[PDB]
Image: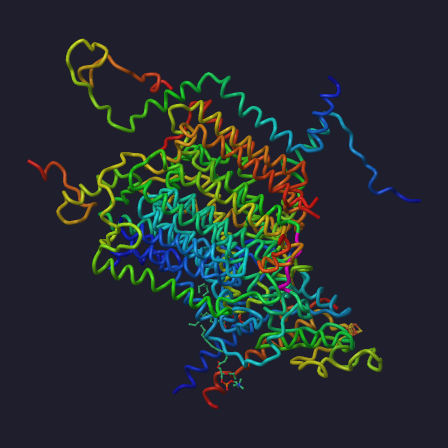
């Protein structure tokens, strides 16, 4: 029956998405520098099909790298709202995940989730480059477990 | 470890390889083993037309020598 | 006189109408003007290739070289009215009245 | 103490001007960098196979 | 025929690519996507205003040089003439006029990208 | 004297491209007149028979024109073979 | 049947011209001119004018490029016009379609259309000429004769292009 | 079987462009101490497939402030011209023996402006409207130099028949006669394809992308296909034009192998240059050709038109 064909097809599609996610950089603080180290020779993000450089129009994943302040929030909102589907947003760093060192500030939102949906919470201050990379791999396995056309066929 | 690039362009080479003989072979395939008779000037076109008429099969690349004539 | 001659002559007639009957735009009008010379270029090439006028084979490009020069200044004039006036819309183009 | 970084003004003999004209026209420092990057191409790539291999701690 | 067949094949192939591109994927079609973009913001009230520019002069001298390039294009056929001396002098005239136009463009600001 | 040489040196340093272009151009006009082979190029161009050499009606007293296409007398281009 | 192509090449030339002259948005007039020139290059080409056809291709698809170059510079506005903006443009367009259609219908029925001059509706393939070219293209050799017989033409042109760059300098100089 | 030959021309060029997107990410990375993509299949061989599938099934966003007609036509023009501009290339037996093949292909090379302008304006964004005019000026201002270089090089070939170009070289590489010219030509090629040293349109500080900003998914990928097909096509053009090869008529495959090797070498030089050099500035970008390249090109053309006359070595017309 139809599950065989639809599962093989959507498995193909989600594999293609999984191995070609394109980050939308978006580094706000030292988490940006650690991500840049994560794209350095040593860990070489670009090996996994991730491309690091991506205009927000052509991109799949946003890494909220650093503290997100009140003045920033509308800009990040307009950036994500324009991001084409599918759009998984990963938050790196204790500051972006929620609060941070500057949790009890006056012009820093207490978490990217209060601004934008977060798909993978990456902890660390900063999350050491390979921890970020592991979060990326976790998102890849999340894309692997994707059943879009299955749910369509079984709606 | 530059040889990791070697597969990458190798298929690429093959990718550019195919348009080479494919056009080359098909010409040889179509024109009775001969390569295509390029007609860059009207004299060449007239020669090709007379060859087509003489062939009697509406195929220019078919050629007959003195055995065709007395 | 076959249909190709009709078609390019008729194309020239409507280019005459389009450029000369202004609607509201100077840029589009000179665009119609340069399309005019395209119609004339094709037309000229037709007889010249037809009649084996071997020398006249060089007349079209010659005819071409000057014609673009006209447009070369036309659009050049277009900017000079544009920076002061603002647009190429020829209905404000009224200061010279008396 | 201190060192002046860029005061090395060039000479103006025929040899020096010919060398500078050749470098400007026959692109040389361009080729210098173009060949250095080639040397880095043939080198051993620095890359750790995550997650099979982890960074030193 | 032949050549026209290749042009037809290419244009139809391209159109199939764009059709699959624009039709196959699915979009939720929500309003706020339509908001335009500029490095995080939107392009305020611009991206169609008249463009106060200066390299217009470079753009027009392009065309003026392109006419002369068209004029000198017949050279490979022209070199096959009996009176090679006149062809040599007159082609050299054409390139000298190219250079003179460029030089007048040069000294009189001109090709110097206006500020 | 000194001023001209110094100006040439400065041009060769300040805008080297300009002097190279001006030089090679200045050659481009003055060599063809000086060169002794341009006449040979004219001979090359006149040698090629793009059209048929339509014969002349024989009536006697044209020894210059060969009677046969294999005849010895007539125009020859052995210089073309040696060239 | 691809017999009538040498006809239709001109026909698509006509109605691509009308929309080009239908006074639409300047870029849409440009598109009309572009399709007209692209289809007219075929008209010259299938008549044997290979070099002239490719020549007009090159120079003209640069020439409309530059007239674009100011259309987005010195001709755009807050609300650029659209090929459907004005109501009259549709009437101009349809008046473009029906005139040559009626005339070609007549030329297909009577073959003696009386519009302006004298014309016959019996295609265009007839007017070609039998013959040969040896080992030289007539068009290329003719345009090559510019440097041997075009004594005055190249001189007056080059002088005009020099004067043209001078005037382009002077009018746009801006004091 | 003509249409079969056509398809055997398009489709392999499509795989070539597809795997160029892998060889660039591998060559660049190895040039900058990165292993490159080697996770999707063996040595990253399958990676171009995955990104292509993603971009096909990525949502193509319609620019709300746009007229869709040009938003769709511009990819059509850019892609179709790029592929049909491969038509008259002298493979050992070129597909279409157009008597003016070089002029044919040079004329079509100017048409990329006719995708750039509609992409930049129709998408209706500041980055798009800037980059449209900037890139248009780039490519048009380098097209002239391409033209005089082509003419000066051809003045020794004999005609515009691009199949006889091989017959021109035969003995010696043509660069040995026009290395000053080719050095300009190649660079101008680098300028016309908008590559990192001369790109100026991406400029990911003040133009971001320039023309392919609002384009997404499929129409967006079509302009990449055009761009990385022009790379291969112009590198192949330069390869035959200057880096000649042998061709025995009884063995057509030999010239095919030599030509594809030359094309790969030149494309690797493209990637080589982009992986090292900084990016030009628009001021310097047009200063490079107006102030420097064009006078040298004019003088070299004068030299190369006077030279056959004085040497009595005019090339055969037919
Ligand atoms: C060559 C490519 C071959 C494979 C083509 C795959 C196309 C995938 C399209 C994108 C994912 C959507 C899909 O598969 O079905 C659409 C279906 C559409 O029906 P749906 O109801 O499942 O959509 C999700 C729910 N709404 C409608 C609210 C958005 O969506 C999904 O499968 C997503 C779950
Ligand atoms: C019709 C619609 C689709 C149109 C596109 C073409 C058809 C679909 C794609 C088919 C190929 C890919 C299938 C999915 C592969 C996948 O997910 O993993 C592959 C995998 C890759 O494995 P991997 O390395 O990703 O595994 C995971 C590794 N870790 C855990 C470290 C993350 O490889 C295989 O399955 C083996 C066979 C690969 C292909 C063999 C041939 C390669 C050489 C020729 C390449 C060029 C010609 C093709
Ligand atoms: S979580 Fe730590 S490293 Fe990241 S932005 Fe906050 S303070 Fe900096």
Looking at the picture, tell me which residue is in the foreground, G50 or A33.
Answer: G50
What x and y, as percent, mark residue G146?
A: 42, 32
Furthest residue to the left? Answer: B70
Kindly identify the residue that appears in the image at 48 percent across and 27 percent down: E90
In the image, the segment drawn in magenta is E47-53
What x and y, as percent, mark residue H158?
A: 40, 34
What x and y, as percent, mark residue G136?
A: 31, 35
User: In this image, H297 relative to C3: left or right?
Assistant: right
Magenta stretch holds residue E52: yes
Q: Quadrant of the C terminus of chain B?
A: top left
* Viewer can see residue H15: no
* Viewer can see residue G94: yes
> What secondary structure do most residues of the magenta stretch adopt?
loop
Furthest residue to the right? Answer: D1
Kindly identify the residue that appears in the image at 51 percent across and 38 percent down: E68
Magenta stretch holds residue B26: no
Please state the total of marks drawn on the protein image: 0
Kindly identify the residue that appears in the image at 67 percent across and 68 percent down: E45
Q: How is the image coloured?
A: rainbow
Among the 4 quarters of the image, the one containing residue H209:
bottom right
User: In this image, G126 relative to A147: left or right?
Assistant: left
Question: Is A82 situated above or below G109?
Answer: below
What x and y, as percent, mark residue A149?
A: 48, 83
Furthest residue to the front? Answer: C98
């Amino acid at each position: 029956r139809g599950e065989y064909v639809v599962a093989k097809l959507d498995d193909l599609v989600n594999w293609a998405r999984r191995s070609s996610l394109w980050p939308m950089t978006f580094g706000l603080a030292c988490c940006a520098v650690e991500m840049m180290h994560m794209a350095a020779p040593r860990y070489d993000m670009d090996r996994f099909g991730v491309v690091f450089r991506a205009s927000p129009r052509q991109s799949d994943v946003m890494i909220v790298a650093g503290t997100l302040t009140n003045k920033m929030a509308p800009a990040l909102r307009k950036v994500y709202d324009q991001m084409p589907e599918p759009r998984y947003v990963v938050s790196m760093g204790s500051c972006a995940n929620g609060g941070g060192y500057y949790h009890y500030s006056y012009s820093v939102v207490r978490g990217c989730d209060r601004i934008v949906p977060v798909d993978i919470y990456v902890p660390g201050c900063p999350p050491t480059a390979e921890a970020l990379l592991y979060g990326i791999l976790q998102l890849q396995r999340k894309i692997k477990r994707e059943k879009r056309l299955r749910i369509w066929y079984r709606r | 470890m530059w040889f990791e690039i070697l597969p990458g362009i190798a298929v690429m080479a093959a990718c550019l390889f195919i348009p080479g003989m494919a056009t080359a072979h098909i010409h040889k395939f179509t024109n009775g083993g001969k390569e295509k008779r390029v007609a860059h000037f009207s004299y060449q076109w007239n020669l090709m037309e007379r060859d087509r008429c003489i062939s009697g099969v509406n195929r220019y690349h078919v050629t007959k020598g003195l055995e065709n004539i007395d | 006189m076959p249909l190709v001659y009709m078609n390019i002559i008729m194309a020239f007639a409507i280019a005459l109408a389009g450029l000369l009957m202004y609607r509201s735009h100077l840029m589009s009008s000179l665009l119609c003007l340069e399309g005019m010379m395209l119609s004339l270029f094709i037309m000229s090439t037709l007889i010249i290739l037809n009649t084996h006028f071997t020398l006249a084979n060089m007349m079209p490009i010659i005819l071409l070289v000057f014609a673009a020069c006209e447009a070369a200044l036309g659009l050049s004039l277009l900017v000079m009215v544009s920076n002061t006036y603002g647009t190429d819309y020829v209905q404000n183009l009224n200061l010279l009245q008396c | 103490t201190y060192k002046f970084v860029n005061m090395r003004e060039p000479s103006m003999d025929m040899k020096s001007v010919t060398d500078r004209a050749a470098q400007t026209l026959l692109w040389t420092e361009l080729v210098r960098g173009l060949g250095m990057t080639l040397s880095y191409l043939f080198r051993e790539p620095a890359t750790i196979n995550y997650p099979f291999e982890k960074g030193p701690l | 025929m032949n050549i026209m067949l290749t042009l037809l094949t290419n244009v139809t192939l391209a159109s199939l690519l764009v059709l699959i591109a624009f039709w196959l994927p699915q979009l939720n079609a929500y309003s706020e996507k339509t908001s335009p973009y500029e490095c995080g913001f939107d392009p305020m009230g611009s991206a169609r205003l008249p463009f106060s520019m200066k390299f217009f002069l470079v753009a027009i001298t392009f065309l003026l040089f392109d006419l002369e390039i068209a004029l000198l294009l017949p050279l490979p056929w022209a070199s096959q003439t009996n009176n090679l001396k006149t062809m040599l002098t007159m082609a050299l005239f054409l390139l000298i006029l190219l250079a003179a136009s460029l030089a007048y463009e040069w000294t009189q600001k001109g090709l110097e990208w206006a500020e | 004297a000194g001023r001209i040489a110094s100006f040439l040196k400065n041009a060769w340093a300040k805008e080297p491209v300009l002097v190279a272009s001006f030089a090679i151009g200045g050659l481009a006009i003055i060599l063809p007149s000086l060169s002794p082979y341009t006449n040979y190029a004219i001979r090359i161009n006149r040698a090629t028979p793009y059209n048929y050499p339509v014969p002349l009606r024989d009536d006697g007293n044209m020894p210059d024109v060969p009677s046969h296409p294999q005849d010895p007398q007539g125009p020859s281009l052995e210089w073309l073979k040696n060239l | 049947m691809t017999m009538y192509i040498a006809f239709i090449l001109s026909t698509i030339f006509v109605i691509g011209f009308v929309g080009f002259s239908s006074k639409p948005s300047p870029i849409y007039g440009g598109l009309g001119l572009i399709v007209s020139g692209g289809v007219g290059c075929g008209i010259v080409l299938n008549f044997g004018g290979s070099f002239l056809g490719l020549m007009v291709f090159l120079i003209y698809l640069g020439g409309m490029l530059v007239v674009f170059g100011y259309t987005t510079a010195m001709a755009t506005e807050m609300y650029p016009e659209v090929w459907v903006s004005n109501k009259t443009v549709f009437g101009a367009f349809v008046s473009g379609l029906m005139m040559e259609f009626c005339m070609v219908y007549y030329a297909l029925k009577e073959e003696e259309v009386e519009i302006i001059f004298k014309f016959n509706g019996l295609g265009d393939w007839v007017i070609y000429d039998t013959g040969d070219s040896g080992f030289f293209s007539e068009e290329a050799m003719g345009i090559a004769a510019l440097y041997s017989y075009g004594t005055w033409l190249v001189i007056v042109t080059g002088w005009s292009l020099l004067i043209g760059v001078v005037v382009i300098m002077e009018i746009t100089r801006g004091n | 079987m003509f249409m079969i030959n056509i398809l055997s021309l398009i489709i392999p060029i499509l795989l070539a462009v597809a795997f160029l997107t892998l060889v660039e990410r591998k060559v660049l990375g190895y040039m900058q101490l990165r292993k490159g993509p080697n996770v999707v299949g063996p040595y990253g061989l399958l990676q171009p497939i995955a990104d292509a599938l993603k971009l096909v099934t990525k949502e193509p966003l319609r620019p709300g402030t746009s007229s869709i007609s040009m938003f769709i036509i511009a990819p059509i023009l850019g892609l179709s011209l790029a592929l049909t501009m491969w038509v008259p290339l002298p493979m050992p037996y070129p597909l279409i023996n157009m008597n003016l093949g070089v002029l044919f292909m040079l004329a079509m090379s100017s048409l990329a402006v006719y995708s750039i302008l509609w992409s930049g304006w129709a998408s209706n964004s500041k980055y798009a409207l800037i980059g449209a005019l900037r890139a248009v000026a780039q490519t048009i201002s380098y097209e002239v130099t391409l033209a005089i270089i082509l003419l000066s090089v051809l003045l020794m070939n004999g005609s515009y028949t691009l199949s006889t170009l091989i017959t021109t070289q035969e003995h010696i590489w043509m660069i040995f006669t026009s290395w000053p010219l080719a050095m300009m030509w190649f660079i101008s090629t680098l300028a016309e394809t908008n590559r990192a040293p001369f790109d100026l349109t991406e400029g990911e500080s003040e133009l971001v992308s320039g023309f392919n900003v609002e384009y997404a998914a499929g129409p967006f990928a079509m302009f990449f296909m055009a761009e990385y097909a022009n790379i291969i096509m112009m590198n192949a053009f330069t390869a035959i034009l200057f880096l000649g090869a042998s061709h025995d008529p009884h063995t057509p495959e030999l010239y095919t192998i030599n030509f594809v090797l030359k094309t790969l070498a030149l494309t690797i030089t493209f990637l080589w240059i982009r992986a090292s050099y900084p990016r030009f500035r628009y001021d310097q970008l047009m200063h490079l050709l107006w102030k420097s390249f064009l006078p040298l090109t004019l003088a070299l053309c004068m030299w190369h038109i006077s030279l056959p006359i004085m040497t009595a070595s005019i090339p055969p017309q037919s």
